[PDB]
Image (cartoon, rainbow over all chains, first blue to last red):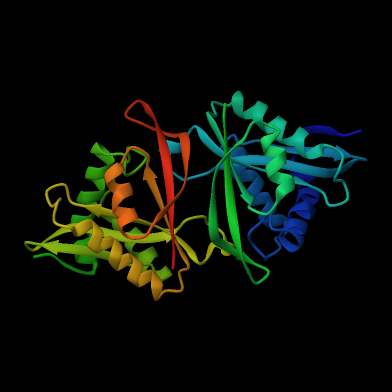
Length: 163
Length: 163
């Protein structure tokens, strides 16, 4: 049984764990520096201030996933465009948590004057691309070797969903 | 004749004028925020610190255009990817200033450990698209209605140049 709800500062340690795991063992985050609670508290506050959602998926009283969206491009002209992110705990995959989280964001976006959702996915992450496509996202394009991690060049596949 | 060189604080008011003009009558900048001298000063100080170039084209003793690049995506993993912008003064068009400014940016980037240059062009700006193509940029994709200005939705065509 999984329940999604708005996150609170109390959920930050569980969100941090998921975040730091992606930083170390995935290409979902293009950064190699783990953050501390204070860093996630600032991140959480920044989202709250802008009215951006932060949703957690609760499994066994623990945070098994989280999702949020925010600026895609920092310009007033993009007011109606937001870039979303969805993360599922390494030990909670295969339960459909990912799709429920993304759907939760789509629903919030649609009611938050959001016209377009943008996804920045590591090009080789087939699971993520298929998840987005299953939700109506369309492939915009693939940027070649724009990122680097694990000592290798990474491509960025962007997708869009008009609301 | 036109000549290109590094911008100094003394070129900031001229740069400001070109920037503000773009904000007022074009889709080159997605917002309606007119900037003052202090803004350009901070902007100029931040780029100088990051080692990002600020090149101006001088014609008839005045700034006939300027160019620069900075972060594309504010993340450590994108350290070798930069987004550039080139602006030609409205009264100095048709002098090949645009191409020369972009070439200068490409040259600087090639010696600044930049692997990819990214162009974010308003979709209908065919002239800009062609200018980038003449310099080797290739289309990645086009985002639909991700921006708004002048009361209408704008599309964003992104292009890339691998160095």
